[PDB]
Image: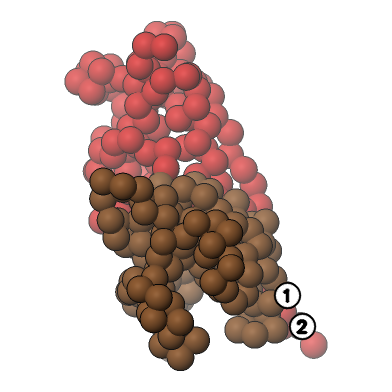
Chain colours: A brown, B red
Amino acid sequence: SKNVVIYADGVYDMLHLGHMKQLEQAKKLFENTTLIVGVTSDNETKLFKGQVVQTLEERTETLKHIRWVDEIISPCPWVVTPEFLEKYKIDYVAHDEDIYAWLKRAGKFKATQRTEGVSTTDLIVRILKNYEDY
Amino acid sequence: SKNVVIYADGVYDMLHLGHMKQLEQAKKLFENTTLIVGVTSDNETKLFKGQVVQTLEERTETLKHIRWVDEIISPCPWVVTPEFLEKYKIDYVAHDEDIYAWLKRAGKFKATQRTEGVSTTDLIVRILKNYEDY
């Protein structure tokens, strides 16, 4: 019944049901939680991960509408640090590990899963299938 | 401070920021509301309105994650009736009128607006612009 602070982060480009289910899962890791969601910057995402359609402001504005999201850190640090966790009093990081090893060492790592086949780009693929190759 | 029951309905295909802002606006029409959202059936939408990518189940599941949504009626009636409003004790219908005339006559119509330029298909148009015509 004590309130547990959960942190999840990501790009959240073109927010879809898969993102929303993952946030739900992070939010429900304990009975009483505060889910903080970190949204990665445009430059760092594009440099280290890949292409992003939506700006930081757009990706953050959309997340604001999601039931499970209690707080947003936008932009968030590209790499989580013990001091970041102390600064925001985070009890657990929820993620789907080499880079995360200190997190599991500290007892601060909580697994979540990705849903496949529910992405925004998957929906466009379905639209295009109305048009026969021949 | 008395609790006002608001009803909004739509297709909610490929849910985007524009839908979410409209739901927010319906939810915030009064201080204390219950926002019921009606999701139109696949057959009726395709027959009377146009093409839908996502099924009723998919469109409803996504809406479930939206902060402003308190209850969902899925599928909802294609045409709102005074008896439907009595049945679910709806105080106001939030919509963006010839068909709605009885609603304004009854004092039960509340306007909301559409945001342009924030749709899911608008995002694919942006992706495609990375590829020069020549």
Tally the numbered discs.
2
Residue B132: assigned label: 2
Question: Badge 1 is on which residue?
Answer: A43
Mark 2: amino acid? Glu
Q: Which mark is residue A98?
A: none
| Amino acid type for the residue under numbered disc 1 | Asn
**Image location of residue A117, percent across then percent down:** 35, 76
Q: Residue at x 32, y 43 (%)?
A: B39
Q: Residues within 10 Å of mark 1 (few under 14, many from 20)?
A: some
Q: Position of residue A131 (x, y in %)?
A: 44, 78
The residue depicted at 73 percent of the width and 75 percent of the height is A43
> Residue drawn 43% across and 77% down?
A103
Q: Nearer the viewer, residue B54 or A72?
A: A72
Between marks 2 and 1 in the image, the one whose residue lies nearer the viewer:
1
Whether residue A49 is situated above or below residue A26 in the rendered picture: below
Picture quarter with the N terminus of chain B: top left
Do we see residue A129 in this rendering? Answer: no
Which percent across, then down, holds residue B92? 40, 19
Q: Relative to B98, say whether B121 is above or below.
A: below
Along the line of sight, which residue is nearer the eye, A11 or A119? A11
Asked if residue A80 shows in the view, the reply is yes
**As drawn, is B72 to the left or to the right of B13?**
left
Which residue extends farthest left?
A: B87
> What x and y, as percent, mark residue A74?
63, 58
- For image coordinates 58% across by 68% down, the residue present is A83
Q: Secondary structure at mark 1?
A: helix
In what element is the residue under mark 2? Answer: loop
Q: Are marks 2 and 1 in contact (CB under 8 Å)?
A: no
Where does the C terminus of chain B fall, quadrant-wise?
Answer: bottom right
Chain under disc 1: A
